[PDB]
Image (cartoon, grey):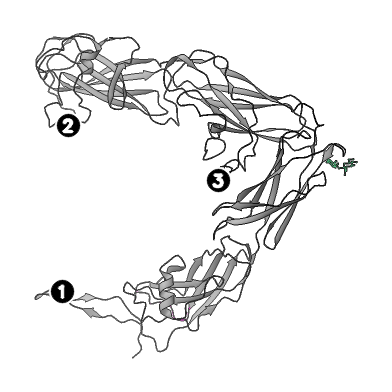
Amino acid sequence: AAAASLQGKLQCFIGSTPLWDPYYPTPVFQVLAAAPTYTLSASVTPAVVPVDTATLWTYNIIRSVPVPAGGPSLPILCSFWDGKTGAAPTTDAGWAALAGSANGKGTSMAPGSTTATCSFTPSYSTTGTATPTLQLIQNSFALDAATTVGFLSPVYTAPAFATVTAASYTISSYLNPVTPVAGGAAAVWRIVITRNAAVTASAKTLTCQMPDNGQGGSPADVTADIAVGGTTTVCVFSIAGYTTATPGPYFATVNVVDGAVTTSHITKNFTVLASGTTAPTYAVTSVVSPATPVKVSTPVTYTFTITRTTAVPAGGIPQPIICEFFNGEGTAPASAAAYWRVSTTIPDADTVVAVMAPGETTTTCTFTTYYTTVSAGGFTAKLMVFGESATAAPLLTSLSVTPSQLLAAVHSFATPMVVAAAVVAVESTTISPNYNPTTPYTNIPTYFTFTLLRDPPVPPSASSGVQFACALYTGQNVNPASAPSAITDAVYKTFTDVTTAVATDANYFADQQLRVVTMAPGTGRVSCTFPTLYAAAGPFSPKFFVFEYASSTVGANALAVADTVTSLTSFTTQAAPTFITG
Ligand SMILES: *[C@@H]1O[C@H](CO)[C@@H](O[C@@H]2O[C@H](CO)[C@@H](O)[C@H](O)[C@H]2NC(C)=O)[C@H](O)[C@H]1NC(C)=O
């Protein structure tokens, strides 16, 4: 019989006891006099998509008979074939197997509804038309790929093909040196080729040729490679033999081919200097702010002015500038070429991209650095300059092309930067609880919070925060059972570590304690809380010490003077009150 709402009854027994009493009702299921039909519509975005780019396919599914109101939402498994890669599965088992991966989506028809949506984002790899095929399965918790039957027969084919167009190429170029000298150093044309979409199958081999270098010559054809997932490649043309017989301005044509696709480009302008003339030479001047000396973590700004002997031609190609700056702290780069450090992104704290504009002589590279260690000898920061574009800079190492060494030797700052240690002081020593801000009660746990402020705050974006070991000797000679041998730095340094001590163990209330506190980056001060318990009332002289901390080892005194003691005001503990707030 055909009915609208129907309920089953499942009753199961372990041994003799039933899991549910009197039974477990099952969700409402509708009985249909005929097989429901599944109408379907498809939409594309964009209708025309470049190769190796995502395209949104949207399928709207409409069911002839609405899902029962009281029953559960109907699970639907959209197995979709983009129509361009491989072949569509021939059996429903193939669709079920394919739907496990990203090519198969899972939606749910809500109860009392007649519509559902399935969206996919395929990325085609070949040019031409693509017509997808989609099939619907049921996503029951126990879906057998073999015996399952899709509700859709025959497999729906979207009557709206997507047009996958071929890839495009944007071609830029620059020259090193920007004004080649005839018969001298060989000129190098660096050609940056950018693809409108990243390659996915494998590395692609662009073929770059230069029919004319402005002088009428034709250098040997070059092949450049673009790696998987990359959108940029560099083609290097080493031309030697430029001549000044033709009038000053010149321009070169370069065509780059990828199979059928051909893209032509013309370099803007450039001038070849007369043979025998002295090649233009670059120099660097350096300024610092503030002046020597500076403290640790103080923002130090270096400004380097790069000056060319002669101005760049007004109509020619502007010269890219890559400034790699080493602040002087740590291991210096091995040589000038070693300064081509691998940078994740171009505008980092060590690499700066500038442009010497045509008709201009000087440019400026600005760096901001923080000095961590202390060196009274002074740090001599250095700078190295290359001529490379920002786009081609990251991938020059991958393509095994030597960056253009734009300087004869590394520029070293004239005056070494003498760096002194930061100044840290104990701002306040609060007691909780306390009869007055100077003395605590007796026979109750009292906590001393010491606040330490560093005059130059730990800079944001620092690798790690600073660490301070704070040592305290309250007195009363109970838990250590003896006074410290001497007030010297070493004796208090040798104190036990209780940074992770809890109230259970006997070290929680120790007359001699040593704790570790980390000043986080972007903070100026830290606090250390020490628990104490004054069993007996009497005069007391708590002693406090601060030390630097590194690699879980206690360093020298943090107060910049050997054997510096922060002596709390002497006090006599008085009786505690018994009133309870509430
Ligand atoms: C880049 O060089 C080209 C080639 O010389 C310049 O185009 C022509 O240059 C000749 C040089 O004798 C002039 O007589 C023509 O008048 C130029 N043509 C045009 C349309 O201006 C071109 O001017 C140079 N580019 C710049 C920006 O100066």
In this view of the protein, which residue sits in the foreground, 499 or 213? Answer: 213
Instruction: Give the extent of the magenta segment.
Output: 63-70
Q: Quick check: is 68 in the magenta stretch?
A: yes
Q: Report if the CB atoms under discs 2 and 3 are less than 8 Å apart.
A: no
**Which of marks 1 and 2 precedes in the sequence?**
1
Q: Secondary structure at mark 1?
A: loop
Amino acid on which the number 3 mark rests in the picture:
Ser
Does residue 162 show up?
yes
For the C terminus, the quadrant is: top left
Q: Report if the CB atoms under discs 2 and 1 are less than 8 Å apart.
A: no
For the N terminus, the quadrant is: bottom left
Look at the magenta stretch and give its main secondary structure. Answer: loop
Q: Secondary structure at mark 3?
A: loop
Amino acid on which the number 1 mark rests in the picture:
Asp
In this view of the protein, which residue sits in the foreground, 119 or 100? Answer: 100
**Residue 31: image location, x then y, percent:** 36, 85
The answer for how far apart the CA atoms under marks 3 and 1 are is 70 Å
Q: Which mark is residue 398?
A: 3
Q: Which mark is residue 21?
A: 1
Image side of residue 71 versus residue 90, left or right:
left
**Residue 294: image location, x then y, percent:** 48, 15
**Which of marks 3 and 2 precedes in the sequence?**
3
Q: Is residue 46 above or below residue 456?
A: below
**Which of marks 1 and 3 precedes in the sequence?**
1
Does residue 436 show up?
no
The answer for how far apart the CA atoms under marks 2 and 1 are is 51 Å
Q: Quadrant holding ligand 1? A: top right
